Length: 54
Length: 62
Image (cartoon, rainbow over all chains, first blue to last red; front, side):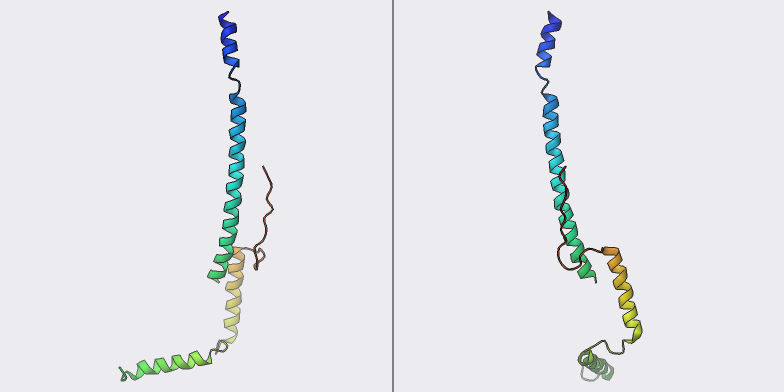
């Protein structure tokens, strides 16, 4: 009885794997966004620096 | 101050250099050769992108 009751009480919370996946994919999207913004900034700064330094 | 003849002499050669700078006077081939050398070095160090407008990225989603 105890084995079965604890098994049920435990498998109740199997949702953490999906919650992980959720926040992990959110993190992936955020890092992509950050890289996009930094890449555009770096390119514009590179061209400006080229002009200024020449 | 109107006495330091070398002072006013340098200022005068300055003024002449100012007026005559239509093109780099007494440049000689070294002028162009250098200019090219460090322009190419700077271009190489910086990049080869479309050195005029903003090149586009067109990223890729995850």
